[PDB]
């Protein structure tokens, strides 16, 4: 036809991406690993390798200037961690109103024949560098008429994204330390205690007619119990901390896109003030300076729609992150207590 | 007044005909309320120390519970360890019937207090003279069998002294971990949660205060859990250390007593060997064997009683510790559940 046109609509939070009219989701599952991808809109599953993921990712970066594109996991439990984060990546892709409609993404998810695969790759390599469309569905209010008010919005988001990048990094660092603290210090303390309870028991077995075999076994049971709890601490991060880190990792990449995204838009804001001022001196034509203004305005709404979409996904993802972490901790400490109440019952006899 | 009788586990102290208990309260003067006394009695630590030094001079073959140190949690831990000391005293068949101990509990006067004090000072029967107080069994046990029993207890007491020291060391380290390490990690986690929430408040119209409040609630929760860990040793670890301290004092009483017994067995074989060679009068060699038989009975009774209390106190120790650990991790789980509902719905 002509070109794809992404729409920006007004909403409760202000400018937002109009939803994908043809929504879908995609599951990721299983010396070359070919991940089995099953999108909702396809009749047959699709097998793609990280190499193919990396191809698409590079295509996305060159295509979308104002949109934050989710980062892939490292190129180099690495295998398991990769799949968890490819899933998180995929979900963020499918739930993004613009990224989910990208033709290169569609070719990535639908193409079966390998002969058509090569063609569809080169076909997506000539678009981009075509930048964007961004039609605006609503009518421009009197509040958004000043690009100054829009630029002030961008500045507050920059400062926000800076401290969020700090808090996320700090939390991700703390979590990774807890993992080692769980495999190390936590396990060690419970195992020194259990080893001590075993030492007490062994000493109590050195006088056969004057010692109770029941008590000596109970204390010995508590010894093995605490030594088993130590192993529970060591095996716990895989249930709660790992998934939290995966979530934080997703937002490391999203937040890392913003510095450049914001830099571009502030450059457009300066180009507007420059073009207009130059048009006031007489060294610039007015209608050309008008085109700069109106274009900067439209992509300003796009950015506003993206920051809006970021907050929307953030609130969903962080809610589920805290919930999932706490539910597991609750389970973990419940399991701990049951071990203790199991070994306490040994002393009833 | 004292007697040693045979039993299922062998030689043992005859039970106190008039058993009792004594509560210790802190209204420094301690409020002591003997259950068999008509009126409560107030005593300071110096009074305990006086009584303690009387027991050392009096009962040589008996293992006397050590008094807590004379020189934070100090002065509070003394109250706990004086209770354990008192309980061991009133539950000992010999020590509980001691006249000076009864004077220490049932003297509500003051002039009579100084009098009874002197009464215990100039006691004719002490040490080796105390051995003529209690009567032994009429049964005859092989002297070699007794020595083997003592030697078995010697090996046991040494290994237990180590295992107790091991657990005592581990527990003391656990107290510091609770105040330091365990608290710190929770404090770090909640602090990070706090920062996340704070950073979420930097873009006011676009961020949910409901979510930020829940996140910062979880932060204050994990910080609260940190302080719970810091306060926890007072509920379980402190009590366990008090029990181990009690038995470290008891196990230290034995080496000297055992050594005296080993010397008693030695002089029996010694005197008899030379009595046969005509180097000593047999009647005097008999008096040595007789003396060894008596002290051997007293030691077996003490070793039996030590085991009797050991299995009780350690059963209760392990029970009290576990029960408090259980309650602790339940209270933690409640803190976590309380903060999870903040994310509803």
Image: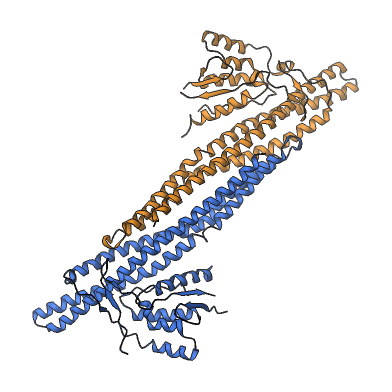
Chain colours: A blue, B orange
Quarter location, residue B316? top right
Judge by depth and name the residue closer to the eye, B27 or A162: B27
Q: Residue at point 53% right, 44% down?
A: B174
Q: Residue A53's x, y, as percent?
A: 45, 79
Would residue B202 be visible to someone looking at this image? Answer: yes
Compared across the picture, whether B307 is left or right of A177 comes to: right
- Above or below, A2 against B127 in this view is below
- Classify the position of the N terminus of chain A by image quarter: bottom left
Left or right: A101 as drawn, with respect to A111: left
User: Is B144 situated above or below A28?
Assistant: above
User: Would you say A278 lies left or right of B275 here?
Assistant: left
Name the outermost residue toward the right.
B277
Name which residue lies at 36% across and 63% down.
A315
- Image quadrant occupied by the C terminus of chain A: top right
Q: Position of residue A317 (x, y in %)?
A: 40, 64
| Residue B302 place in picture, x, y as percent | 71, 27
Q: In which image quadrant can residue A308 be found?
A: bottom left
From the viewer's side, name the closer residue of A53 and A201.
A53
Res. B184 in view: no
Side of B243 relative to A204 (left or right): left
Q: Between residues B135 and B143, which one lies in front from this camera angle?
A: B135
């Amino acid at each position: 036809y002509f070109q794809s046109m992404y729409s920006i609509e007004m909403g409760p939070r202000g400018p937002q991406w109009k939803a994908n009219p043809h929504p879908f989701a995609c599951s990721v599952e299983d010396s070359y690993i070919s991940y089995k991808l099953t999108p909702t809109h396809a009749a047959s599953p699709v097998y793609r390798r990280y190499k193919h993921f990396d191809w698409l990712y590079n295509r996305l970066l060159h295509k979308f200037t104002v949109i934050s594109v989710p980062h892939l996991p490292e190129k180099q439990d690495f295998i398991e961690k990769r799949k968890r984060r490819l899933i998180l990546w995929m979900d963020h892709m499918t739930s993004h109103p613009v990224l989910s409609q990208y033709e290169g993404f569609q070719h990535f998810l639908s193409c079966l024949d390998d002969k058509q695969w090569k063609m569809g790759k080169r076909r997506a390599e000539k678009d981009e560098m075509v930048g964007a469309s961004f039609l605006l569905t609503f009518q421009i209010p009197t509040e958004h008429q000043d690009l100054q008010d829009v630029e002030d919005r961008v500045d507050t988001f920059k400062a926000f994204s800076k401290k969020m990048d700090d808090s996320v990094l700090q939390l991700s660092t703390v979590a990774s330390e807890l993992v080692r603290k769980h495999v190390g210090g936590f396990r060690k303390e419970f195992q020194k205690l259990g080893s001590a309870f075993q030492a007490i028991s062994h000493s109590f077995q050195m006088d056969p007619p004057f010692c109770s075999e029941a008590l000596n076994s109970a204390i010995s049971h508590t010894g093995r119990t605490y030594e088993a709890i130590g192993e529970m601490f060591a095996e716990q991060p895989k249930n709660d901390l790992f998934q939290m880190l995966d979530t934080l990792s997703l937002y490391q990449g999203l937040l890392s896109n913003f510095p450049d995204i914001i830099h571009l838009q502030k450059g457009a804001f300066a180009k507007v003030k420059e073009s207009q001022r130059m048009s006031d001196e007489g060294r610039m034509v007015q209608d050309e300076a008008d085109g700069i203004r109106r274009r900067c305005r439209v992509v300003g709404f796009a950015l506003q729609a993206e920051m809006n979409h970021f907050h929307q996904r953030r609130e969903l993802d962080f809610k589920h992150m805290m919930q999932n972490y706490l539910r597991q901790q609750i389970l973990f400490y419940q399991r701990v207590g049951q071990q203790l109440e199991k070994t306490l019952r040994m002393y009833d006899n």
